[PDB]
Amino acid sequence: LTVASLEALSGLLKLFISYFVGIGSKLLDHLLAWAQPRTLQQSTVQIIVAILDVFHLAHKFMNDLMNALLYLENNLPFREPLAKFLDPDESFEYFFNEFSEITTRFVYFVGLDSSLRAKVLESLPRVRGLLHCVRFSNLVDLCESLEELLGELLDAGVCLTLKRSSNVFQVDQGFETLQLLYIEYFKSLGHEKVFNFIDKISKEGLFDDFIFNEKCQDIPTVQQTLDTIIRM
């Protein structure tokens, strides 16, 4: 129980005493700032890094960040990089650390902090994770915590499960649903109409229906899909 007492006493005493001179204030501030790197460079990383990093909101930052980031990122890690960086590394850290627990560190570390990393990381998980459901068993935090208008608007016009499961912010749903529904419904062979109508209707029809339907545009998808699918 020394982590809670040491982290709570050091974070509470340093946070409550750091915002209160000459040699005493400079020696106490320099001793606390120089002493926080020894405890943050290695349970107690969340309270120590959160209280120490959020309390006071050049060789010590580069040496502690380079040594802690290189040793913690190369010795595996998500709490040190996410907590120390949240106060080209995504491709090398995610690819090198995931190509050898990888979902939480890769999704939390890569999503806690741009089209190549989001498109390659978000698109490589479907084939790399399904080549051996996906949204419920994977639960990627980068798509929900990071960027959704570019990937959803650029990729919406496989996508029904990630878009419908990850979409459940009015500019992305309105612009992506209106542009994808108008372009897909006006640019018209069964894969494009079935995938666009099922993905747009299933992804756009999921408090959002009562506030967004006040329902008149649902007769075109059911009438065109039911008449075209039943007649064809």
Image (cartoon, rainbow, N blue to C red):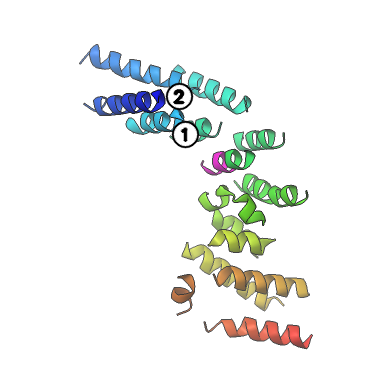
Q: The N terminus lies in which quarter of the figure?
A: top left
Is most of the magenta stretch helix, strand or loop? helix
Classify 10 Å Cα crowding around label 1: few (below 14), some (14-19), many (20 and above). Answer: many
Asked if residue 175 is positioned above or below residue 38 in the image, the reply reads below
Q: Nearer the viewer, residue 123 or 130?
A: 130
**Quadrant of residue 58 in the image?**
top left
Query: Is 102 in front, or is 116?
Result: 102
| Snapshot quadrant of residue 96 | top right
Residue in view at x 57 percent, y 66 percent: 176
- What is the x, y in percent for residue 64? 49, 21
- Please state the horizontal and vertical placement of residue 137, each as a whole percent of the image: 64, 52
191 falls in the magenta region: no
Q: Which residues are magenta?
A: 107-113
Q: Which residue is mark 1?
A: 83
Left or right: 139, with 57 as reference point: right
Residue 58 shows up from this direction: no
Q: Looking at this rendering, what residue extends furthest in the left direction? A: 21
Front residue of this view, candidates 8 and 206: 8
In magenta segment, residue 110: yes
Residue 80 image offset from top left, x and y in percent: 51, 30
Label 2, label 1: how far apart the Cα atoms are: 9 Å
| Residue 34 sits above or below residue 197 on the image | above
- The residue drawn where x is 53% and y is 84% is 216
> Which amino acid type corresponds to the residue marked 2 in the rendered image?
Leu
Where does residue 83 sit, x and y in percent of width and height? 47, 34
Image point 67% across, 55% down: which residue? 134
Q: Is residue 105 above or below residue 115?
A: above
Near-viewer residue (183 or 60): 60
The circle on residue 40 is 2
Element under label 1?
helix
| First of labels 2, 1 by sequence position | 2
- State the SS at label 2: helix
